[PDB]
Image (spheres, coloured by chain):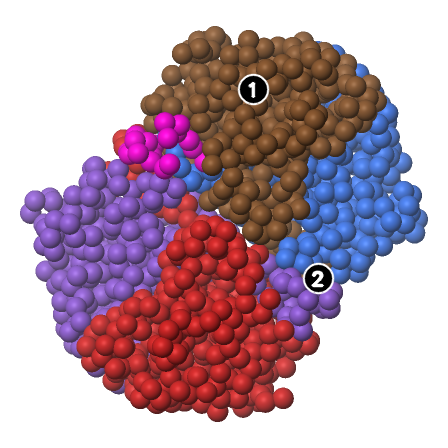
Chain colours: A blue, B brown, C purple, D red
Amino acid sequence: ALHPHEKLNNWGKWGDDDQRGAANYITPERIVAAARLIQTGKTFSLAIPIDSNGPVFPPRLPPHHTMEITGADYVADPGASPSPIRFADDYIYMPLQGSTQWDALSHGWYGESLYNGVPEAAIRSSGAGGATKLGIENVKTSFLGRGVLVDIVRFKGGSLPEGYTITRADLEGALAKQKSKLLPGDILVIRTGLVESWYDLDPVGRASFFLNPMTGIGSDTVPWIHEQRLAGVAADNIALERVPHLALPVHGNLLRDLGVYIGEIWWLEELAKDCAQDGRYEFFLAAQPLYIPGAVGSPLNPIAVK
Amino acid sequence: KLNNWGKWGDDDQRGAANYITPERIVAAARLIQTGKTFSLAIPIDSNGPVFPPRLPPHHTMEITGADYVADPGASPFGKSPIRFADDYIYMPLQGSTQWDALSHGWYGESLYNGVPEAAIRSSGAGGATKLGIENVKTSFLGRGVLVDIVRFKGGSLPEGYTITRADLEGALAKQKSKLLPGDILVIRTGLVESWYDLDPVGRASFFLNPMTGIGSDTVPWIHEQRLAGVAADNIALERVPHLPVHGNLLRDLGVYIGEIWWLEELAKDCAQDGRYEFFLAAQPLYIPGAVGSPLNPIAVK
Amino acid sequence: ALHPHEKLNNWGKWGDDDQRGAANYITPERIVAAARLIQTGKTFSLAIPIDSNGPVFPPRLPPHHTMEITGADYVADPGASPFGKSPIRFADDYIYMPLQGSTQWDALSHGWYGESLYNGVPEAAIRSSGAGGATKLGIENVKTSFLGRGVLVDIVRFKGGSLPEGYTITRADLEGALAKQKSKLLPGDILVIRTGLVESWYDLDPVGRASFFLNPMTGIGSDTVPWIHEQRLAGVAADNIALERVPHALPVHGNLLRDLGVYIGEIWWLEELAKDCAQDGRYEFFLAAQPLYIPGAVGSPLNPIAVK
Amino acid sequence: KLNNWGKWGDDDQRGAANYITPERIVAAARLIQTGKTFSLAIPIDSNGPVFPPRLPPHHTMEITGADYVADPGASPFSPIRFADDYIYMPLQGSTQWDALSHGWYGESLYNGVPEAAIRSSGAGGATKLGIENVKTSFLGRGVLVDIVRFKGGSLPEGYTITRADLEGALAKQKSKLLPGDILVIRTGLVESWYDLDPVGRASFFLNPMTGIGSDTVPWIHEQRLAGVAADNIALERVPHALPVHGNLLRDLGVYIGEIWWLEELAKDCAQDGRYEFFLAAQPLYIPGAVGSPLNPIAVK
């Protein structure tokens, strides 16, 4: 299930000091080509709402929004704070892996080294620099380029059964049905439907949700991802890889060996409906991370533009 | 009383974001000819400028590579050959590069389009139940234009200098830049560029000084130009003494305010190739009920 | 049954500008008397651990502890210099938590009904943190209180070693248990009630923990309120989550906080204290249950210590 | 080399907290004769001293009274109306105890605990020497030593408080230290903070700061103190090297308290001549933490 590093890796492909990995496949020419896909100006946000009500993998805590001062305060007391202008201010506490996200190459690995031989000792507490190598700031202008939706739900004409493993054949079959063709630097966005089952669940159902096996991609997608020179793979599930009822070889192979970024908890329902209606599954994607030095991932609001 | 109330209907919660139309996004995309990209964000960390008493953003790890050096058997999520690092942030949503929502500021008892201030509540009571930033989760992706006031003036701006309508129009003309409806205007004042070289005393003084920014007479012009948003590389956008513009932009016009953007590298590039118009991806995070958002604006040429 | 305010309240008892409520029952003489109960020097912490594993009423977040710098950092990088170059090595940490997220006192600013809080304080006085928080009845008003005499009433043992799910603890139960224990309450006492509920939480799996908060929970009922008033208690704490019985109106919250100005303690841990009291027969002790000094807050975490 | 490793056994994680015994708590309780109490905490808010780069504590509300003014129908969770709140803070961000896991030198902490035992919270935090090991400690006898009044005025900037000063102050007060005591030291430093403007507050931490010096450590050992707390930020004198931190936390297993507020207690003791008191200075029960906020209460 875990592909041997020596037979399948991108270490050294972009130099022995590179910290960007497969983001290097997104070059200026790939961005210009993506821009030519903005023909209609349609836009879609591929994020879930950042609030305390969304899926987040235990033991991670849900994002938590609080206000510092509100409109209600001025109803209560017109004389709040220091001028005729009235204002509201707020705060957030959240896991950076707590919502729609990119995971950096510093997020996961196996053994004592990360992508391109970076030692795990380089990934420290925040007060010691956090991810001092392979931090998400290395890709603060990346993931703006060409995106491609693969709608596995519509390809399967049904429910992915509980814990279904999405294969190479499934991905290629869906792209063929769509008459889509991948290019180097593409960000692949996979619709599994899993997040579309969350919000209707009651509290017991939401506990069960994470105890269940969960649909996602399998090990035989990893050579394909390498062959297609994708920069990142995102999905509308929580762990990208299929999760059983714990090896996680796809995480290890993508992040450490290929230097390919992982996107999770994206929201693809409205994008997928639009692509079904206009037949265009390739689009311009603005999926830049936040500029967070030493972080091992970021929340974002990916925008698909057609 | 100059205002846009009702312009887009009595139920509208998006304001001047409605100037960004699909056709205008298509036009902006045609500006992507080289593929050059520039992040207009400052780093999110505890060392950036933030208006007191706002807390600096604060990053912590939940588990790190160092933990596995210390204890190879670390199993945050159970026994696995896979090793992981996870992290967290606490920050003001007004604590870094930001958009301010229309729910961020007003005067009197009403916000944009007659929304009562009673609609803007604690997070447990819905936060901004109207005019929350989620209303523009697909906005601020379109055409951007830089106006470089430092370059126009030929020197660093005086402490507390009021940037006038004449300065904005004059600088755009010298650049041969033409604004279009729906544009996001990004203003280089230079103020934030001074921050990172400051020592702790300098950083305290930074917020005691008057601070350069736009003045009241820019508001009719911003209205006439049908801008969707105005952002700057200062902390408060408008000039601050040792806030009429906030009130008029957010409440009366429904025009968004961007603060603590980073424009130094973009400004050098635009001076070189002569192009101050670009495609801008400056979408907010999707945070329902929030009164603003962090972001990472990307200028694309 | 919500007890009518006019028949049962302490408004004005300690003046119409008072913000401390029943904490005023704890007097220097009552503290001196409580200190005389320190005869053996046995100590018991009545707190649950502050971590992300404890009971917290949804949608409140679990407390969350993170490190800023750790020993592991120096294993990975001996030269780690967080402050900076030094032979001394440091570890530092942070917490994010609800102040109602663990073992707690709830201030009189935490709960009320209608438009007024204890002693006629307008609800408009309780604002966002940036506008002063609880500008009246904040927990700082009792930064020196809740150190005095405590009395355990072990309702679990009184009822034979267990309480049914959702059981309503009555006046008669409280008096009956105190009589069995040969305990006598005095004005100013902090009453600590063992319901056993928190003793069932930690073995639950994620589904069980979700169910825990969806179903009825044992606690005190409405007819305990006049008794609490009678007895001139300063505060009432329990090892459940809501103090009063919760169904599958919450009049007790309203009557205690608003009408009487009596403080509510929740998610205390009483199992070891109760075992000790069963063995030595002493249910009255010195209690150090001071809140944190947090101006404008509507409650506080704490580590209550029973001293015998 | 002076140290307590092994004094309380190889498995011990409590250090000098073991000097506080039941009999010593009983003795301390007899000092409660007036029933007067004093909080020795500063307010937890964003306005207090906190050593950079630590951030100030930050209080926010989840729901407030104002919400029901704006919207009578607010239903966060009823006729009952509720206010709920949150705190984000460094555990070293206010009045505090520092655990034995907070500081050391070399690769070993108190009693030979490896520094590899002190990990991220997701990996157990301080898996040994966490503050939970003393969740019932620091309730016992406290003694104030008022160095400000002993010196007859405010201490000079960066003044090193010596063994002779501590002994001299105790002698002037007619105080007698006993084993198990918690020593509480008034330097006055925190009493200068709140009147400072933002520039002064920046300078405050760049300046040398008054505190105890190296020659106090053998005396702290000989006196069998459980912990030493002060109303400065770092306990030991800080220059522009921190041997006292290392010797106390790693070698002796003695706890360090910082940012205590002693103004009102010190005034009371000067008036009635009593500098010994019952102290309730328990930490919060935070497993794997390397310190804790608290509200220490002195009772006389």
Q: Let me know if marks 2 and 1 both belong to one chain.
A: yes
Which of the 4 image quarters holds residue B2? top left
The picture places residue B94, in percent across and down from the top left corner, at 52, 36
Q: Residue at x 71, y 32 (%)?
A: B264
Question: In the picture, residue B22 is in which quadrant?
Answer: top right
C39 relative position to A167: left or right: left
C-alpha separation, residue under disc 2 versus residue under disc 1:
53 Å
- Secondary element at image label 2: helix
| Left or right, residue C169 beside residue B36 | left
Question: Circle 2 sits on which residue?
Answer: B66
Q: Position of residue B190 (x, y in %)?
A: 65, 32
Neighbour class for label 2 at 10 Å: few (<14), some, many (≥20)? many
Contact between labelled residues 1 and 2, with CB atoms less than 8 Å apart: no
Confirm whether the magenta stretch covers residue A85.
Answer: yes
> What type is the residue that disc 2 sits on?
Ala
Image: magenta residue range: A72-89
SS for callout 1: loop
Residue C199: image quadrant is bottom left
Depth order, front residue of A165/D295 = D295
Q: Going by the image, does C189 lie left or right of D140?
A: left
Quarter that holds the C terminus of chain B: top right
Front residue of this view, candidates A51 and C79: C79
Q: Chain of mark 2?
A: B
Residue under the point 40% across and 12% down: B1
Question: Which residue corresponds to mark 1?
Answer: B164
